[PDB]
Image (cartoon, rainbow, N blue to C red; front, side):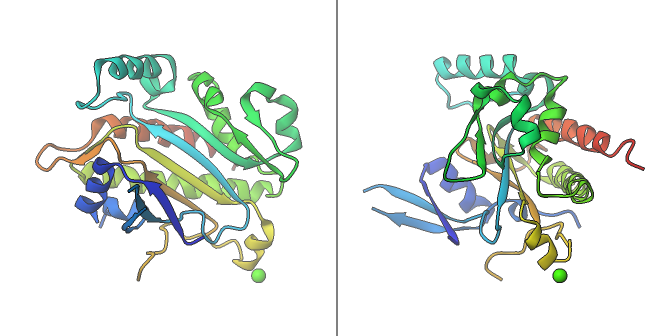
Amino acid sequence: GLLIFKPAFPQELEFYKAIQGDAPLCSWMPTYLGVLNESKQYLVLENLLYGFSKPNILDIKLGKTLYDSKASLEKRERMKRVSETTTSGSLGFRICGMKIQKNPSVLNQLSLEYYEEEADSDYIFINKLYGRSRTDQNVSDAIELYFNNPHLSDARKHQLKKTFLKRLQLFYNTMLEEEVRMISSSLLFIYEGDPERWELLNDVDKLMRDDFIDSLSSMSLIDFAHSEITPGKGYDENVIEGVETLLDIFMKFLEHHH
Ligand SMILES: [Ca+2]
């Protein structure tokens, strides 16, 4: 599963084509490889899950404003409602979903309405209703829940929080330099839930993802159907505000853990 096939939206295709010592934006994105035709067209992308044994996935939507210019006022109105009623409008980001290995301690406290199990795996899908119902006060706990893998020691969970903080510092620095406007893009977090793989790699976790063409965790930026390059227009303040909040949250994870 080296590759992903995503239905092509012309604006997302144009964004990948336009893009592809602070890191450049492209280094956060999946590698775009081309298109496949059916006709139905698909974007062919690097699979960000490739190489993980038990990937644990967190999708976060970036921005207070959640519509672009091309939006019909019907969806413009729907998107203002989403922003106004979730952490998007207050904090600049919201949890969109997760797919994580179930932790018995977690499952006991989480409402049945917030997730979908299966018999065929140890994985739960944490749904949109969960992410939309997070408040400014409990959203930090929701992120700590993501990391609460039953197979990882407290030392490894902490390492990951620290590594992702560093990625957020680097991503913030990238965003100060990029002249783009990105609407409803996601940061995609992935970490390795299999501690045999932590053994194999001796707990060494690359800050930046290996260039695909020529990791125990990764942070990526995905979903560019409402993105475009905007040279001369300055940095994306809308997105950076969400990043600023994530930085505060992740720095707080490190408090008290001397
Ligand atoms: Ca080893």
